[PDB]
Every structure is written in structure tokens, then in C-alpha cells.
Image (spheres, coloured by chain):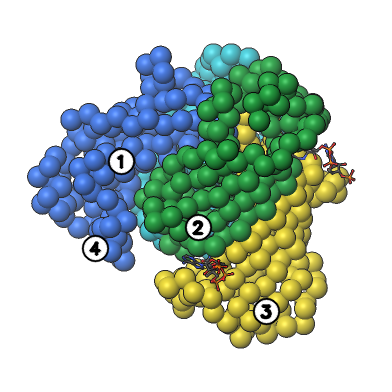
Chain colours: A green, B yellow, C blue, D cyan
Amino acid sequence: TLFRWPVRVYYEDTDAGGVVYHASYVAFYERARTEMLRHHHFSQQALMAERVAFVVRKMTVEYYAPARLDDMLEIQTEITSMRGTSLVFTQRIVNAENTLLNEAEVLVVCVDPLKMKPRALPKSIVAEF
Amino acid sequence: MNTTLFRWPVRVYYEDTDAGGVVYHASYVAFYERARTEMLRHHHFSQQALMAERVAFVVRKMTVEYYAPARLDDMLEIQTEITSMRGTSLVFTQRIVNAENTLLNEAEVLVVCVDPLKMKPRALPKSIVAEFKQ
Amino acid sequence: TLFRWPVRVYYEDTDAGGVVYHASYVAFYERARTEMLRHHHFSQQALMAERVAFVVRKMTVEYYAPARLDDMLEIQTEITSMRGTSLVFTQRIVNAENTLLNEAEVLVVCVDPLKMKPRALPKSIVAEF
Amino acid sequence: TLFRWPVRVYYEDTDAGGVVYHASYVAFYERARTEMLRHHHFSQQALMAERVAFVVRKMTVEYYAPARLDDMLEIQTEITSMRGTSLVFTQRIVNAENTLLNEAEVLVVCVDPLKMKPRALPKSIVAEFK
Ligand SMILES: CC(C)(COP(=O)(O)OP(=O)(O)OC[C@H]1O[C@@H](n2cnc3c(N)ncnc32)[C@H](O)[C@@H]1OP(=O)(O)O)[C@@H](O)C(=O)NCCC(=O)NCCS
Ligand SMILES: CC(C)(COP(=O)(O)OP(=O)(O)OC[C@H]1O[C@@H](n2cnc3c(N)ncnc32)[C@H](O)[C@@H]1OP(=O)(O)O)[C@@H](O)C(=O)NCCC(=O)NCCS
């Protein structure tokens, strides 16, 4: 199921190349994942107060086309695969003209911070997705 | 393909950390960018200068594999090789190790040479090809 | 007239202390100024074609209380001063409980982005302010 | 005593205007303070042993001239004042030609990471600096 999250491009996100810095896309993707979780009632640091957190294990990003200042982007997020301790988010970004700017596949592993050891996924999250 | 490994040190500062107590995963991406830039600089090329010559380098595809976390005040070494080279693009193989030489993570980066103000692929400058010819 | 802009704290804005990095606040302030100008139909990628920009000349931030991950903040922004070439933004950040986290006074100069020289303010900006 | 710290400008620090994003300077200044303390063996490790953290109370930055991609800058840092639970950093940034790009005055409060209330400056710190 698809979750959509709007993102405005600000000066902070751009570089001297006249486009969005390639790492800023990575941050945009994280917000989208965060907001999708929130859409299913989750708060990631009150959730780390119960010592459960999410870390990125692997990420593959393809940049097809650039975003620019004040572009209103849409980040699209899906959970495509689920295992015992990890999640696979399939994500993509489009602009106002529905041009496909880029897309990412993010392997996220459920850990808990003070150990950051792979912990089994919370039972509630399994029920949701 | 000039195989020689280029090494670049990076100190982890507060700005690179998150509430999790480790380095933010996008900061690794910037660290990789810095090392590629320094590798180019070591071979006598400035991207600021190349910009006005209508030459820029943009990331087309990037794969990052996070094995182990970096923390505040760690002194890291970014390692950078060019493994593939084509007309308008080339492939970087990079990885990050800490002081104990623990492999923190590694990346493969596809960089494309473009004309920044029209954002279309262009042949790598001959002098850059010359430096990484072999 | 006061202008309000909501901002969500994400992982990207936090540091190892578990609170928002103080430079992230600076970025938040910039967003609000941009959105404030936008609200008066003053977009800045549109005007860079027009070779006109707003660069920060002086910024003073005073910090009182911290913000944490997933906090929904509010940036309050008002223009308090104006001269032929410059203008002053008075800004502050509060949290959901209306606690004052910090405040900033930002001096901004209108310049040409080519040689970066001080130009006089567009008579339309001084009009709607 | 003046402490110098080099900082290279990268793409990450720049914006679409072709110059360094004004917030990137704030981070540069912190690195320099961090490195200044490190020079006197006051590493984060040393601070945690004192259970001491440093937070910014007030900061005034003055932007005079822009830095650009590939500029090698120098951050110049000095402690100009020290009081009970705080101390004032005076910082400047110059380029390779020693042109003054911008400067900052940073009031830093000595806090306690438990809680972050004012804590008296460590004896070693007040003795290390004058
Ligand atoms: C690098 C770049 C110029 C390569 O141009 P290219 O020769 O068209 O390369 P590709 O064909 O492999 O691009 C893949 C697809 O994106 C399309 N594309 C390229 N530039 C585009 C643009 N400006 N707008 C919309 N689509 C674009 C391509 O047509 C292609 O379509 P298809 O595979 O579905 O048929 C282009 O992909 C690009 O601008 N990527 C974004 C770079 C970036 O911003 N990186 C982050 C900052 S470093
Ligand atoms: C996510 C993580 C807990 C995976 O758990 P895992 O049990 O090690 O599972 P994996 O099989 O994927 O391990 C991958 C490799 O990383 C190594 N590794 C994991 N944690 C390590 C550590 N703390 N120190 C050194 N190596 C470590 C593993 O040994 C493994 O290498 P190997 O083939 O020699 O065994 C761990 O790899 C990790 O912490 N990665 C970094 C996460 C991160 O910092 N992301 C950025 C912030 S979100």
C-alpha cells in the first residue's frame, strides 16, 4: 500500500551544481519512512525509549533526474518485503509534473540502540503490514 | 584503469551524529563525496573551476552497504578506487574503515559527467581521462 | 504581520545528545523566511533568473530550551526593520507546548548574485511590507 | 592563545547560489571549537570523564564575504572570556588569501548531560585557559 509525503526543496538541500545534493534525497526518503510509520501510529524515539529502533542496513538509489529549489516533491513509500528482523522499503520521488526523479530500495533492520543488535520485529508492526 | 587506492581521513563531528548515538546514514554519503572530490583534487582538478567550464559530475546510481556504525570523534579512512571508466561516466568503488581497520561500510557509485546548465551527459574531459587512463 | 510555519524534527536534525543540532535551527529559520516571502508571492528560484537575492549579513541566535526527535515545532517570523538595501527578520521557535526554544534576529541584504553586490530593495517588496 | 583549524569547502556545504550555505559556517565553527579543546587534551572523552557538556547559549555570526566550493578556509578560534559556568569563544574565518569571510561570537554554557543545568567550569579548563 502506497504512502505519499510532500517535500519542499530549500536552499539547504541544494548545492553549487544548481540541483539538490545527492545525499539530501536520502534524508527525504527517511522522513517519508518516518511519516509512513506515524500514519500507522509510531513515534521513533519514544519508540527508542522502549529501546526499539530502525537502522539502515543497505540502500540503493538511482538518480534519473534532478530536483531544484522550491520544487514541491512527492516521496512515495511502500513496504515490499518483511522478515524476522528486517524491512524492505521501496521508495521513489516525483515532482509536480509526475516526472520520476529517482527511486530507492532501503533495507532496514530492527535493532535496539544501546546494543544495536538485530532484535526481532515488534509484534504490532508485523500485524500492521 | 588506474587501480591505485586513494585514502582520505575524516573526523566524525557532532553534526554527523544522530539521536541514536551513531553517524547519520546520509553523512556517510557525504563522506564518500568528499573522498571522490579529494581524489580528483590529488590528480589536479577542481570542480568549482570545472563548473565554469560547464563540466560537472553527478551521481547516477549509488549502492551503500552499512556493516558497522561510526561514532562521535572517530577518525575514519575513506578509501576510493576507480574500477570502471567510460566515455561520459565512471564507476567508483569506495569503503570506510575506522582506526582498528574495521570495515564500517562500502559503496559503489556511478558518476556521470554532464553539462551542469543543460544537465545532459558529456564526454569526460580528455585531461581527466588522461589522468585515469592507466 | 506575524507568519507561522510548522516544522517537524527528524533524525537528520538531531545529534548524539538526543536533541536538535543548533545549526539545524538555523536551517529551520531560513525555511520560515522563505515561506514567509512565498506567502507574499516572493519566490526565490523565480527571482534568481531575475538575478536578485537575499543573503544573510548578520544572524544572532539565543538558545533557551531543546527540541527532540519527532517534535512538531512552530517557527514565528516577522519583518521588524527595513532600509533601501536591507531588512531585518525577527524570528522565534516554540514547541507544541508553546515553550520558547530559541529566538533569532537575522539581518538580510538584497544583492545581485553574480558579483554579490548590494542592490536596493525592489519597490514591490517595500510596498507589501 | 589563538588556535587555527583548516576547513575544506565541499558540495555539501554549498547551495544553489554558488556559495557556502550560511548554516554550514555554524558547523565549521563548532568543529574548530571541538578541535581547539582537543589541542588542550580536552577531548569529548575527557569532557565525559568530567561529566561536562558544552552547549551554545548565544551565537552572533557576521557574514562579510562568501566562501565557495574547493576553498581551503582557516577557522581562527580563541576564548576571550571565562566566568562561573560559561565561556565566550571569538571566532573568525578567512580564505587562502586571508580575506576575512565572516566572524562569530559564541557564548558556551558548561552543562551536565544528565539534565543540562549550568555546571561550574572544570578546574583544569579554567586553569588551561586565561
Ligand atoms: C545523469 C543524467 C544526465 C543521465 O542522462 P541519461 O543519458 O538520460 O541517462 P539515463 O538514460 O540512464 O537516465 C535514466 C532515465 O532518466 C531519464 N532522464 C534523464 N534526465 C532526465 C530529466 N532531466 N528529466 C526527466 N527524465 C530524465 C532518462 O531519459 C532515462 O529514462 P528511461 O531509462 O526510463 O528510458 C540524468 O540521469 C540525470 O540528470 N540524473 C540526476 C543526477 C543528479 O541529480 N544526481 C544528484 C546530484 S549529484
Ligand atoms: C545493522 C546491523 C545490526 C546488522 O546486524 P548483523 O547481525 O551484523 O547482520 P549482518 O549479517 O548483515 O552483518 C553484516 C556485516 O557487518 C558486521 N558487523 C555488524 N556489526 C558490527 C560491529 N559492531 N563491528 C564490526 N562489524 C560489525 C558483521 O560482522 C557483518 O560482517 P561479516 O560478514 O564479517 O559477519 C549491523 O551490521 C550494523 O550495525 N550496521 C550499521 C548500521 C548503521 O550504522 N546505519 C547507519 C545509521 S541508520
Q: Residue at x 22, y 29 (%)?
A: C2
Q: Residue at x 70, y 56 (%)?
A: B63
Q: Which residue is mark 1?
A: C35
Which of the two residues, D24 or C72, is positioned nearer the viewer here? C72
Note whether residue B58 is visible: yes
| Structural distance between the alpha carbons of marks 3 and 1 | 43 Å
Q: Secondary structure beneath disc 3?
A: loop
Asked if ligand 1 lies within 8 A of label 3, the reply is no
* Residue B94 rendering spot, x and y as whole percentages: 74, 59
Disc 2: CA contacts within 10 A as few (<14), some (14-19) or many (>=20): some
Q: Which residue is mark 3?
A: B86
The quadrant of the rendering that contains the C terminus of chain B is bottom right
Q: Residue at x 48, y 36 (%)?
A: C24
The quadrant of the rendering that contains the N terminus of chain B is bottom right
| Structural distance between the alpha carbons of marks 2 and 3 | 25 Å
Asked if ligand 1 lies within 8 A of label 1, the reply is no
| Amino acid beneath label 4 | Glu
Which of the two residues, C32 or A9, is positioned nearer the viewer here? A9
| Amino acid beneath label 1 | Glu
